[PDB]
Length: 30
Length: 33
Image (tube, rainbow over all chains, first blue to last red; front, top):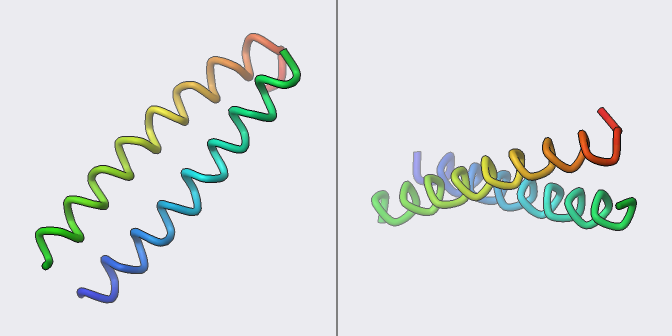
């Protein structure tokens, strides 16, 4: 379960980075 | 250690939702989706 939590942290971190990229992409449009 | 990992998930998930909310607002402004 330790490994599952670790994988989810890595997964969420990647998702957050994507969303941060998206914010930047969307800002640039503006 | 479980507690630490779980706290990290709850932290990142909250950050995720705040970013999603912002992306949603910006998409509307620029008239994306």
